[PDB]
Amino acid sequence: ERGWFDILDDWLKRDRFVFVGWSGILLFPCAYLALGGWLTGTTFVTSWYTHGLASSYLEGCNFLTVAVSTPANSMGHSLLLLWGPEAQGDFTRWCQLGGLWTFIALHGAFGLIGFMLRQFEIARLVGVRPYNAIAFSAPIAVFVSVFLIYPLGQSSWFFAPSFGVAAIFRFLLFFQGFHNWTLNPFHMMGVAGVLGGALLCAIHGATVENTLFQDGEGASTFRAFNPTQAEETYSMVTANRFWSQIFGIAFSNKRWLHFFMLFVPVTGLWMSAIGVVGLALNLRSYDFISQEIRAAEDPEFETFYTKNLLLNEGIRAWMAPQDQPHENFVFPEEVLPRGNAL
Amino acid sequence: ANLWERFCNWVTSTDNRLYVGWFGVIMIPTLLAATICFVIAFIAAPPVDIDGIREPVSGSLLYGNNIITGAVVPSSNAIGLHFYPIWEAASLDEWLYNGGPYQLIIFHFLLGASCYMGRQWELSYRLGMRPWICVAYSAPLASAFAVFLIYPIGQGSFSDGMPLGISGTFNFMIVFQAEHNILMHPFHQLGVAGVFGGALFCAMHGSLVTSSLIRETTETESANYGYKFGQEEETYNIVAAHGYFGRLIFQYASFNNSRSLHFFLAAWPVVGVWFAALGISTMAFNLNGFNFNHSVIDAKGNVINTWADIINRANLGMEVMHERNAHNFPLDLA
Amino acid sequence: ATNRDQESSGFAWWAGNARLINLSGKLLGAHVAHAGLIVFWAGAMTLFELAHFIPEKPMYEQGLILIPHIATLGWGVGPGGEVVDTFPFFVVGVVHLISSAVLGFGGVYHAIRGPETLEEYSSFFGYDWKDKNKMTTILGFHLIVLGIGALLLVAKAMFFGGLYDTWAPGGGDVRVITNPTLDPRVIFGYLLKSPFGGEGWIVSVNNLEDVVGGHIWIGLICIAGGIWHILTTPFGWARRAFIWSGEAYLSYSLGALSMMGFIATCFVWFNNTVYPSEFYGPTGPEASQAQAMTFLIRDQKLGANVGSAQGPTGLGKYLMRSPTGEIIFGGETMRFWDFRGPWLEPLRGPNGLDLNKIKNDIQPWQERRAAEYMTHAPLGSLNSVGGVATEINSVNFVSPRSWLATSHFVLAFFFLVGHLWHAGRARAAAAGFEKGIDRESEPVLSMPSLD
Amino acid sequence: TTGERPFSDIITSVRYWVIHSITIPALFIAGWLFVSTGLAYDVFGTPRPDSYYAQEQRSIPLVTDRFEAKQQVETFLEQLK
Amino acid sequence: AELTPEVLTVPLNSEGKTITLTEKQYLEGKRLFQYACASCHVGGITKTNPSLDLRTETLALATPPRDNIEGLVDYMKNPTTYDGEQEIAEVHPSLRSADIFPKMRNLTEKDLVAIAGHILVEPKILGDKWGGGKVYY
Amino acid sequence: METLKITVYIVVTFFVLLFVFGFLSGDPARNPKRKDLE
Ligand code: CLA
Ligand code: CLA
Ligand code: CLA
Ligand code: CLA
Ligand code: CLA
Ligand code: CLA
Ligand SMILES: CC1=C(/C=C/C(C)=C/C=C/C(C)=C/C=C/C=C(C)/C=C/C=C(C)/C=C/C2=C(C)CCCC2(C)C)C(C)(C)CCC1
Ligand SMILES: CC1=C(/C=C/C(C)=C/C=C/C(C)=C/C=C/C=C(C)/C=C/C=C(C)/C=C/C2=C(C)CCCC2(C)C)C(C)(C)CCC1
Ligand SMILES: CC1=C(/C=C/C(C)=C/C=C/C(C)=C/C=C/C=C(C)/C=C/C=C(C)/C=C/C2=C(C)CCCC2(C)C)C(C)(C)CCC1
Ligand SMILES: CCCCCCCCCCCCO[C@@H]1O[C@H](CO)[C@@H](O[C@H]2O[C@H](CO)[C@@H](O)[C@H](O)[C@H]2O)[C@H](O)[C@H]1O
Ligand SMILES: [Cl-]
Ligand SMILES: [Cl-]
Ligand SMILES: [Cl-]
Ligand SMILES: [Fe+2]
């Protein structure tokens, strides 16, 4: 068996500086177009006709404020293809209608698929187990739930996150004010997985570096390691005693330790994804009913929970007219919620 | 050996199930006091006039809270930074109304946790280890100091310290955003790179090591039984893990040195969290996030909004609503 | 290239300066050159500030931090802190800049041309870190130098023009101090004050007599201590308490400097005596109080009875009681009632703010000052947009009090981190395991199991 | 190594710089002119500072119909006189 | 939209005469207003007394009228309360009180005209934002 | 309250004194290798 397919497979799997692979055929153009689309938009392209915002270096934005913004709410969930019925093949109009947003979201999605396929392909060639790809399932679930499922549940792509620093900050604040997203136990598990993962990263790196064996004469200890060496470079036994005596418990099994390092942040991200799927439908953890019944009846009952809801109400009333221009909100001064003086 | 020597030997002993040590001598009573007060208060404390306007906020389970809404509530704005121990109050009922437990707990806790850091140094010394795990722990510790002590000092009141509760924590974050535009501050941004990055590298390292485990078991048993505590040989093949990751990106983007790799795993989240802490600690003195409100203007002079201005509208909502009965004059100056 | 690579020195390039630990000549060079960098910055930055200085605008509207330091000493200013002569600032700048050339010259010489070690060249200048007596002697020389410095401040205050006194009778002005506080009950009294609200430890120093007398005490103490350390060698208990090595001494100094940094942060944030609001802008507390004052004045002009006006919460809208009964300003500024400043004190009686004085005695200059301070509160963005976080672009302002406080918190924090790093390392190296665990002598392997 | 010439070799060679001392500034100048001639505005349809609003108008030209969005944009553009 | 001569044409006095400012005059006006006035009057409001703003309509109802160049220049020389009843130079920046408001010391007549021109032109650009406060940000 | 204050002061002083005298009791030598750090 040495036909054109096998010859191609040979070329695709050459050991070169940048490995290609069959997965490369999907991954390279899609990742390139997504990145190039973002750079192109943030440098040159407005959001005047979709959002009423300037969004590019060309208009005077900086790195923090540039974005490729979502299409107008009136576009619905249009794929907004360049040759589609909205832009009708007109590149300029396509940019003005927000076509770069779906360009980037879709090429980005297919590129992420390509990258996970790359993780599988390389693992298979090299003869290792595919846990890196498996762990990548968490980035996939986040991207798909946030940039795709979420706006698909809402009225249109307009409410997806826009690709920009400040734009993303706005997304966070929208979620606080409208969804009370910090109250959601799926977000809370996400937070624990992220902060716990960061904790594990720090503590494991630090522990290894402070239980090193002296394997050289240098006071800078990095050179006293050889990639081909059979011996552990640090003492698990000493590490175990230290942590047992400091914290009460300690790892004793290195395999379990590293598995756990995969488990914690990967599971956290998956949990946050589930919460966002509910938010696509406005299925929020917004309230505690018992709290509201009590507070409604008793004007002296106050908790941090009720205090945060008043903040959410402020966010909604003060941000909506400019953040949701298609609604044509006109909120007269007298109806705006405000405490004393401010 | 005299009694003082014997005592010293026991205190500093490497054979105790939990290490005590001189830092531990301060750590143990202080943490016990903060813990016991916290538990009792979280369950049973009456409402606390956090903002000094005779508007008591209920934080305890027995007074209408669940786990998510419950908190130990910061001491009164009328107190400010004044030291308010039990013995400064005419009565326990007074002490509780004014938020005395918050101060007792945060002070004992900050002292105890500082001592926890010292104790990590100390045990490392008793065992012949290198000393810097405690430096790693300085990052979360500095963060605690920032929200419980430095922010209050800068703003002039422990009423603005982070509440000891889940929803209270969220409250602290939202008001902080209204007042300092923390999302647009580069130190918080480095913080986020620090924790996202930490989680990423945690997963990455976990996955690479797990992927290169050397076969030592059968299909019907956990692969974890392939490692035995204290065995001299490494349990995974770093050469294979590096062959993999090096081909995933390119060769020179991957670590071949386990020591450099682990130092990176330490340094990335620790440094990023150091900046997170410094963010809060400097916004404590009102050096705030970037302000690009109305930065973009057209030829006539019309304001052209950017995403920064939408952020600004959100922040205005938070600002005008927070502590709705506490401001009498137009500017919220702390 | 003696000791200038990782193989000979044991230290990688990124820790290259550790290669200098036992090379006293070159290390002397590093130190002198660094001093040159500091003095350089002081001079250059002073000339930069002066070039960018408009005399009729307040200093704090102009991003100045050094000119305020000079003016506080009484140079260049008159009544109310008005600039009457910029020449002193010019002089301080130029002389520092010129001196930096000298220091840099010495530093470069010792660092790349002079003797690499000093010991064979001179018993006096040479040293062993582990030689306790030599260490205490050099420590002594330096203590005497510091003491002389403190006394130089005393001399400025008492014999060479005085200091700017925000508290001078009739309004702030430069004043000669003729009766420095010498009473140790007062001087060390500050040292025993709580650091919490209404006390504020040494940060509470509120008059120049105390500042000057305090510096007399510090001068004499430093000279006496220096003599002590030249004439003595460390006692047994000290010898047994400390690690005696270069990295250890460094770690000690790092802890000391961290402490001083935190202190300076608080000083510049709260104190308005040795950091006059005329030059540095109002404190946070000051500006908050000033807003309350401003609206009390406005509403009372309109006819309000500010003593009896009940606010929405039941507390006085303008005036209320502190927890010990003193009459103070209301609203959120209830937190800041410990504030004291020359524009406010004339309205203060025995029981706090006095309603009669408020009704009858508020002068136009007090209204002005309160308006100025209220509208120069130390709030502003990283790109120097003045005001709260939601304020629009228009005013280019971040208070010098904020710049100074934030910079010194960051520096103090990282210096604490450095103290931990170098203290832990000095311990490990003195004990002999800073490079890692001896595989054939792992201490934990000789210990009984925990269970 | 995978066979390609080491980068450190390439970027320290004379010929590399004979080539790139031309190609790099040329690209940089091309991008400059893309902005400076105003071509970027026309390619991407980004408003010039005088083209966000007509003289007296203060309402955003928001797209409100999906399938005639193009013509709406064109109408918005005409109304800038 | 552009900053046209029409936008830059504002009332000189209360008798129907206009003056057309130059673009450079407009820039000078914005600069001088930030320099001497914005600390209290950012955005056309008044931080130390929010009841009184710099809206053109508000200025027209002042005594004497302050919705023209002459009125504004005079205000900067000899400010009064809103009803014209008291002179307030002692607590409000003016040339008359340049001694106690030192930032007024370098302001020339040309400068005052520029500031007045700024105050009159801005609302023609910004509308309700000018004098509007945070509600219109 | 006065009794509570006195008591707490005594307790705190006791523990601080333990800390200080403890670290003064030949601490550099309390390590597994080179003890003579004097
Ligand atoms: C190779 C990887 C790759 C992948 C997976 C994608 C995927 C996509 N591109 Mg991208 N694109 C790529 C490379 C890729 N692109 C490259 C290299 C360029 C530069 C030329 C582009 C330039 C580009 C532009 C300008 C646009 C896209 C768009 C899209 C989206 C719609 C595509 C579509 O409907 O095709 C439909 C075609 C197929 C699925 C081909 C299937 C062929 C079948 C199986 C064989 C039968 C064909 C038949 C015999 C032909 C008969 C024709 C006859 C009847 C007339 C989709 C996400 C659009 C978009 O993003 O909108 C937001 C869009 O506007 N792409
Ligand atoms: C305050 C900053 C500072 C200072 C004063 C020093 C000083 C020193 N370093 Mg260190 N170092 C520093 C920061 C500093 N370092 C930093 C940031 C790094 C990381 C990049 C290092 C990494 C490092 C390593 C790896 C090593 C040193 C070494 C040294 C010593 C000898 C250097 C030598 O032989 O140069 C030779 C250099 C030259 C001959 C070139 C010219 C150098 C001169 C001094 C520049 C003068 C310029 C100035 C403008 C002239 C003004 C003149 C005018 C006054 C008349 C010297 C005492 C070495 C050492 O310890 O030796 C035992 C050593 O191996 N350093
Ligand atoms: C004590 C330190 C200090 C303080 C408080 C100030 C304060 C000020 N400076 Mg000065 N200055 C300093 C040092 C300082 N400077 C130094 C070292 C230089 C030489 C570079 C200058 C040269 C200088 C010039 C030329 C100017 C100023 C100006 C100013 C004013 C505006 C500052 C600004 O906009 O910053 C912007 C904010 C930043 C640049 C952010 C810096 C963030 C740093 C990089 C973070 C670093 C963290 C930490 C140090 C790193 C640790 C690493 C960790 C891993 C261990 C403000 C009053 C301006 C002025 O108004 O003059 C009238 C002005 O034009 N300064
Ligand atoms: C940290 C300060 C310091 C110290 C401890 C030393 C120490 C030394 N220097 Mg170096 N040097 C320094 C800074 C320093 N130097 C500076 C700033 C310069 C530039 C002028 C030099 C330029 C220099 C040269 C060119 C040479 C030395 C030499 C020496 C060695 C012999 C010194 C001697 O015998 O003088 C004897 C002492 C005197 C003659 C009396 C000095 C009178 C002083 C300067 C009056 C002012 C004192 C007052 C406290 C100054 C305060 C300054 C403050 C504001 C910063 C000795 C190791 C020699 C050497 O190493 O040969 C191998 C040598 O040739 N030095
Ligand atoms: C006890 C030390 C001490 C303290 C508390 C002060 C305080 C002050 N000085 Mg003074 N000064 C000192 C020593 C001190 N100084 C010395 C040694 C010199 C000579 C260099 C000076 C020369 C000087 C000048 C020229 C000026 C001042 C000024 C000031 C005032 C403003 C500056 C500031 O915020 O510093 C804050 C102070 C600190 C952060 C230091 C805190 C010291 C702590 C409490 C002790 C540290 C001890 C150490 C770690 C222990 C060693 C170990 C031992 C136990 C064995 C402030 C009241 C300014 C002024 O008054 O303007 C009118 C001014 O212009 N000082
Ligand atoms: C930079 C300044 C400096 C430094 C680094 C030193 C360093 C030293 N001194 Mg010296 N000394 C100095 C200045 C200095 N001194 C001055 C200015 C004087 C005159 C007052 C003296 C008078 C002096 C005497 C009489 C003695 C020393 C001794 C010593 C040695 C041991 C000290 C010790 O154990 O500290 C640590 C301090 C202790 C162990 C004591 C109690 C520790 C508690 C916890 C202190 C709590 C302070 C706390 C932080 C609160 C701070 C605020 C508070 C002040 C309100 C050590 C070499 C001793 C020695 O061996 O001489 C040969 C000694 O007997 N010194
Ligand atoms: C869209 C589209 C497309 C594509 C395009 C592309 C592909 C593009 C690319 C593009 C690109 C590819 C661009 C690039 C850019 C870049 C840049 C713009 C850069 C910059 C940089 C900088 C600025 C730097 C910075 C920094 C950092 C980052 C860090 C360090 C520091 C510093 C600061 C240096 C097509 C045609 C297909 C179709 C249609 C549509
Ligand atoms: C060792 C070393 C180092 C360092 C070094 C250093 C750090 C040095 C320093 C140096 C210095 C520190 C220098 C300085 C100099 C200065 C000068 C040279 C000055 C001059 C001045 C002048 C000339 C002035 C003028 C004037 C006048 C008189 C008047 C007014 C105006 C003016 C300004 C024009 C390094 C890192 C590299 C590495 C290697 C080793
Ligand atoms: C000038 C002035 C003044 C005065 C000041 C003074 C007079 C100061 C003093 C100061 C002082 C008099 C300080 C002291 C300090 C001390 C210290 C800081 C100590 C430390 C210690 C240590 C660090 C130790 C450690 C340890 C332990 C604990 C255990 C054993 C081991 C060891 C040794 C490691 C006044 C305020 C009036 C006003 C303003 C001006
Ligand atoms: C206010 C707090 C108190 C401040 C006091 C500081 C003033 C300076 C005097 C400090 C005196 C230190 O006195 C210190 O005490 C202990 C107890 O006897 C001594 O004795 C210690 O020696 C050995 C050292 O190998 C220890 O193992 C042993 O447990 C202990 O007996 C120290 O060798 C001595 O140095
Ligand atoms: Cl709130
Ligand atoms: Cl208020
Ligand atoms: Cl109105
Ligand atoms: Fe590991």
Image (tube, rainbow, N blue to C red):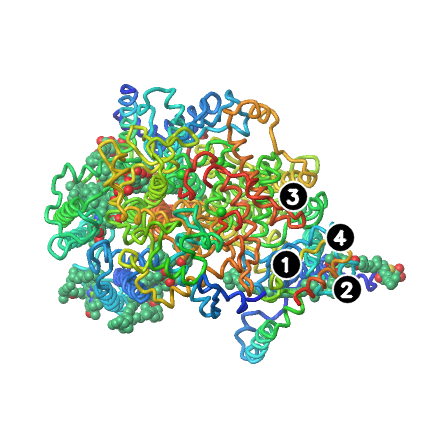
Q: Are marks 2 and 3 in contact (CB under 8 Å)?
A: no
Secondary element at tag 3: loop
Label 1 sits on residue:
A48
Q: Locate residue A57, reporting x and y percent.
A: 57, 63
For the question of whether residue C7 can be seen, the reply is: no
Mark with earlier residue (2, 1): 1
Numbered disc 1: what chain?
A: A
Q: Is residue D31 left or right of residue F30?
A: right
Q: In this rendering, which labeled residue sits more in front, label 3 or label 1?
A: 1
**Does B243 sit above or below residue C33?**
above
Disc 4 residue type?
Ser
Specify the label residue A78 is tagged with.
Answer: 4
Disc 3 residue type?
Arg
Q: CA distance from mark 1 to mark 4?
A: 19 Å
Q: Are marks 2 and 4 in contact (CB under 8 Å)?
A: no
Numbered disc 4: what chain?
A: A
Numbered disc 2: what chain?
A: A
Q: CA distance from mark 2 to mark 4?
A: 15 Å
